[PDB]
Image: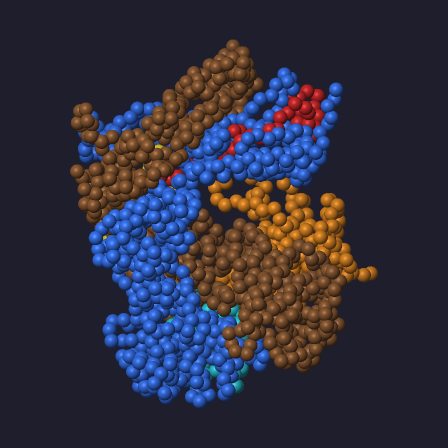
Chain colours: A orange, B cyan, C brown, D blue, E red, F yellow
Amino acid sequence: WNVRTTFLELDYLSDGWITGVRGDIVTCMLSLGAAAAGKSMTFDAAFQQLIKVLSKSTANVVLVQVNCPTDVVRSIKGYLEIDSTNKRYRFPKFGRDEPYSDMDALEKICRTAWPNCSITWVPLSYDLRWTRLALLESTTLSSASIRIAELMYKYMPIMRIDIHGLPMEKRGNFIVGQNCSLVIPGFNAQDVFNCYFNSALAFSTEDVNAAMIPQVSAQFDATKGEWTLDMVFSDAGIYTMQALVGSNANPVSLGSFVVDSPDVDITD
Amino acid sequence: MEVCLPNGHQVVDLINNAFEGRVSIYSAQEGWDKTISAQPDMMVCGGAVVCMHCLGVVGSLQRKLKHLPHHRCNQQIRHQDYVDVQFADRVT
Amino acid sequence: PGGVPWIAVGDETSVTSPGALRRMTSKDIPETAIINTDNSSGAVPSESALVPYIDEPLVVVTEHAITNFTKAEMALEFNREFLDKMRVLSVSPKYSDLLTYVDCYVGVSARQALNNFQKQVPVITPTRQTMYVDSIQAALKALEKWEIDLRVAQTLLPTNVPIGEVSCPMQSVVKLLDDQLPDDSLIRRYPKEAAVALAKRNGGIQWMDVSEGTVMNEAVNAVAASALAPSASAPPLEEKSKLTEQAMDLVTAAEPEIIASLAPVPAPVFAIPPKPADYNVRTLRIDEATWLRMIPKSMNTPFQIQVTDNTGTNWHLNLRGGTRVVNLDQIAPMRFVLDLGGKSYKETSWDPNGKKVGFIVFQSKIPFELWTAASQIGQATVVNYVQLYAEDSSFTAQSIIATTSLAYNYEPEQLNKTDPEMNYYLLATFIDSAAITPTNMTQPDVWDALLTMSPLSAGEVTVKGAVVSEVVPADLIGSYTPESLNASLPNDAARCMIDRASKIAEAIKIDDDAGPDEYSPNSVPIQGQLAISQLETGYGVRIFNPKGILSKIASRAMQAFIGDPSTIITQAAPVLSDKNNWIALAQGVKTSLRTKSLSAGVKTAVSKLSSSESIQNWTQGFLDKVSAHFPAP
Amino acid sequence: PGGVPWIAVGDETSVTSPGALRRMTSKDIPYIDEPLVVVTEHAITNFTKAEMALEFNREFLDKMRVLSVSPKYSDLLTYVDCYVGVSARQALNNFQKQVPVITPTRQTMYVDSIQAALKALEKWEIDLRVAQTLLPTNVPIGEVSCPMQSVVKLLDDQLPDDSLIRRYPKEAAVALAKRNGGIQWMDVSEGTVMNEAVNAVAASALAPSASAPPLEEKSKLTEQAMDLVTAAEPEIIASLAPVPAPVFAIPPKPADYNVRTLRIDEATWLRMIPKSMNTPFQIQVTDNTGTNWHLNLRGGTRVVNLDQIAPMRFVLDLGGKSYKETSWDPNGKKVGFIVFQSKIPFELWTAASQIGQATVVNYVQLYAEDSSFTAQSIIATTSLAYNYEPEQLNKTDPEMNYYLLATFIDSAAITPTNMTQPDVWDALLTMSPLSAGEVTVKGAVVSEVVPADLIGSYTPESLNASLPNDAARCMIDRASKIAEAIKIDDDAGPDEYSPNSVPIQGQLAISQLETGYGVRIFNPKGILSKIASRAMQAFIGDPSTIITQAAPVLSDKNNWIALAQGVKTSLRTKSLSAGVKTAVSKLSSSESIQNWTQGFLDKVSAHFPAPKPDC
Amino acid sequence: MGNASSIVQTINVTGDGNVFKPSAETSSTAVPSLSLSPGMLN
Amino acid sequence: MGNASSIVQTINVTGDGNVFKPSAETSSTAVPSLSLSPGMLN
């Protein structure tokens, strides 16, 4: 090899080695669930252990594939089954089993470890760019398999943690049609916000009434120096936020949040 | 310039000298005098001079310091982490 | 080339595999046998019944061996006259007449040898090589007394001058040498042989020829002399080369990269043979020595316990307030020796003479502070004990204890260590077959005595009193106050680092000769770092200094390092506490040394020349004395 | 040859010509062009030896399917005719045919291939070393034997469970046969056995003869002795002329003193107020942080003087002292250093007007514990630290005087009648130099020193009260190496003349024959031989005798110079020789070790018994 | 070493006729060191 | 490297296009020491 390329033979959830490695961006994909199932532990304990070992590292960005639902819990017949009483993902195509947890627990763990981090849930649904890694490798694709992959990614997102980020807080119930609030600190009275939903400008704060969301409002408090955003959503999904400060042409990026569909209980 | 932490016995000496009302505290606006209250910048712990923004040993009593010497500071210590010793010193 | 020769297995000059080659022997080359030796040295027997006829292998002789054995024979040739006088080895061995030149395959293994065909290689058998070495070794053995007497004759008076030339009439030298040389010496018996040998060794001694008259230099080693001789402006070449090579060896031994690492390094690779250390356990302060424990003071209820050693004998002893013990966990193997000599322990109610002091080891799950009423003692036995003796003391109306060497070895492997909860303690105190009444004996212990600890391992390292598996050498810089250095254990990492850095200090002092406040190639690495650091942005007031001030500060830093090599460890050191300066200096030493081109310093050269001229003047004065007190006819 | 090859750019060439030469590149041999480098002979030979170091283990390297083809360094070298040299002038003066050249890329690939093989062979190498070391396979002299089946049984018995020999026994056998010519394996197909070793020259170099030690040991010992004496630098320590301090000094060592117990007349780096003043006084001193401390001065107070002392570090320890008085208690008190600088001498001080500018540089708190004696308390160990670096002070004005004091301090005024102790100097002080290029004599810095006058001048007390950077300690540490080298190079017993003691004898004879003041005396040669022998023995047993005053023979200067020159002129004229007693003792010891090895092999054969003869 | 078996072989580690006879004149070295000084190699 | 002066006829010290690429393989060496032992010269 031409540049440094090191291979180490040791389990990464054990202690005594993270002091002595050099890195800034950490990648863990499709390994945490199987490792946690092998040692027969809950997903919360596995995530807690992983964050404990990564606390002492020198990383700046963490990219972890996580077992956690970002919508209502539903079963995809033949490809994934969800057991809710005992939190359990079952994969019948491979005959495998893994545990899973909720967004609240993981967010609380990360916020305890890094008090001012920014957590984003990478949106890959509705996007066709990853196809560049398939058609250009002499591989044949079909549309139905793509849809199955989208629906499976709905429950296995990539959590991206930026260690030195901008805190913000969620208040209301992020459900379709309800009232949900954002509290954003560390900004002045001349700043601008804008939200994005699948590469389309959902709303902004420069022109409040020109939004595409049913109801948006924004207030500023000077004593607390905080922006309060009140919103009522219409479509479920994952929304991203950006902030414009002063006259800068490069916009500082905040995290992202997930808006959920209403209940699915029907009777006759 | 890079700095290191103080030892245990120096912290013990700081505590003992603090609950007795004799700490020497440096504030930029006030100097080495402790008549007028201010936010601390340097503190003398067990024969060493430590910066109060990171708690890393920045000098020793053997030399005189006009103001906070240039160094590398992580600046991850806030005023609510050590106000207890200031309270003890003022009250005593 | 080296190795062994190889031949074909009989194939018609078509060798296309390593399976068609076999190793050559003396049957394939009959001239290498034992019966074909020229036997000019008479070593091989001439009787045909005594010379064996068997097949020996062959090996290849390389040019290095040829030249070195050829010079070994000329070592013998320096004394041909005396060797003739004893009828020993009348014909020179002439190594080159033992080898046999063959065109063959050369190598150690067949696969390599197959692809390497060489012409005119010299081979020999082990037997003939051993015979040649034996002949030279015997000739050397026969000359021990003669060489010693020759050296005495040469060294009786100075025959070498550091620089220039001196002189004296030879008749005076001969008279002095007759007067002073020992009677046992062989010089008196065989003068002319000694004269010729000395004339060969030394070019100064020249013997006039009676028949013709010509007197001329006859030494055989002028080239080496010119390599040793000093020019009138510089030192000799060989001395400079030797000094630089020694400095490079010290730098290599010091491992400059180990002591500058920014990543953890294992304990066995970092360690070195340690040294014992001495302490006074009573005089130590508990918050500084993290490896001691003490029962809380102001306790007003002394209690007594009983304990039995490995022979079952019962012993009584008492614990009170102030008693101290030592943690025997997480300190690696260690040997303790305790000596009470010079202390009194005398009261009106108790006298030490005739009493016994012992080491007692405790195992319990309860911390030593929370001990009372003997119910918390746990499992315990007596390890060792010794009886005291009293003698008169310098202070009037007092007496002192004679010497002791109470010893104990602590090896962590034997003890079970099953329950992490379990705690181990060690104590030294009085014991007696009768219960010691608390009123009579009030001393908490006998820890007021000299204590020597010596490590029992070489792959164990602690920090501040607790063992670690790895260390970061760049993280020990400027992290020890002086009080924490007189209370560490002998297997500490600070001592290892200091001893490793002492070699760098020695190498720098050997190579460099600079006065106070003078720049040197070994002090600019700190200067560059200081400049770049003073430009940067941190927190606090910046101060800018020119190049002169920075050069002076860097030079003072290097001098303070050389004079005292433990400043790197010491906390709040002025300039050497920063890790960047240490790393830069350690890395720059190698580059500074490797790029010398047969050179030295100006001050060294000038002082050396002045010294040598003074030496020649003194030598000439002494020779004038000799020629004046032993008149020539 | 060496350096690089060159090519003439023009027809016109001479010894010293402008231009006329350009460096050769890969274009000029028969795109990327790289430079060429001329390869010497030393590199070729050493790299070939390195290759055969790998080739010892061919059978294992072939079982594991690595290193199918050998490196063969002599393929990579290209032979060409060209100007050769490091610079253009040297190339112009030289011309050689068939010099070998190579490019850096190929050399790097070659060395990387060797290193990769050596990395892959490591565990195998350690395993063979363990197998060779487990039982004695070498003997200093002679020949011992043991049945092979018993040996293999023992190896199978005691070898580790992960040893790679247990997986490849035949390859390990062949490897051991290659390394050691004692282990021979019979050829089954023909029923013949003989030595199959490839190392038979170094074996002869390392082998004793019937009556003499090995050559390698003698050569190594002589080279070591010469290296030690060369490092000792005889010319510097024999000089009769001034030599600069940076040249003479070598890295110093700490020293331990007690200030109170020293006497004033011997030690000239101390100043004490006269005891006739009879009255105390008290002063107030402000430290660097503005704190006020009150301390008291009285009669008998001692201070270290900092004027003519090199940059030095003081560390003080009070452990074991009592300092307990009727109206004072050491527990909870404070002790510190004070640095005075004033224009009034210390002995004249009577009032606070004389104390000059003062500052409490450092201070600690005293903690006391019960001691061995009854109703007695002693102080815990302290390490009070100060670094006298002169250049931080104002040394421009000459009238200034500097002093150092160590005593009790307190925030309140100290009552004179409570404490009558002058200071705390009655404690163990450790001084360590900070400058390795400055030297003092008898307590004052000297610009240059004369090595021929230090010898035979110090009384024992003066040598005791020396500072760590004294020139005498440099002299001692520079003569100790000569002493060690002579001891390595000699085996003379009591009263036996040796080539290392006779220069003193010649000097003594000449001095005896001279005329001088006093009652003249005469001696034979035997008495002088004995006297020289005793003097040399005393020197070897104690290198600190040259400087001690009124020494028997070594206090003189001519004797020292003669000995220093004799060391070189004796070591340089040896021929691979050794002492008679050393030789005979080595022979007897080697034979005893051989007997012990043979007995152990007999024990090994008794257990692990070999199969009985079949028929 | 160890014990083994083959149908055809050349040497017998556990067999008879092998020699183990250490000697002073034989000794055992491989390649303890080499001289690779920067001054010598250029 | 030379300083405080620039000359561009042949080698411009302060010009563009120069390389400063330290490496472990290239290293830096001179002639520190040689073999001048008395027994080997003769």
Hey, which quadrant is residue D167 in on the image?
Answer: top right
In the image, is D157 to the left or to the right of D27? right
**Residue D512, relative to residue D256: is it above or below?**
above
At x 52%, y 52%, the residue is C273
A237 and C325: which is toward the camera:
C325
Q: Position of residue C454 (x, y in %)?
A: 56, 58
D422 and A185: which is toward the camera:
D422
**Residue C103, relative to residue D202: is it above or below?**
above
- Say how many tags the image has: 0
**Quadrant of the image for the N terminus of chain D?**
top left
Q: Position of residue C227 (x, y in %)?
A: 28, 38
At x 48%, y 82%, the residue is B22
Residue A12, visible in the rendered structure: yes
**Residue D496, relative to residue D237: is it above or below?**
above
Q: Position of residue A36 (x, y in %)?
A: 69, 53
In the image, is D283 to the left or to the right of D601? left
Hey, which quadrant is residue C428 in on the image?
Answer: bottom right
C410 and A189: which is toward the camera:
C410
Residue B45, visible in the rendered structure: no
At x 25%, y 30%, the residue is C218
At x 24%, y 76%, the residue is D399
**Residue C408, relative to residue D485: is it above or below?**
below
**Quadrant of the image for the C terminus of chain D?**
top right
Q: Position of residue C94 (x, y in %)?
A: 38, 22
Q: Furthest-right residue in view? A: A268
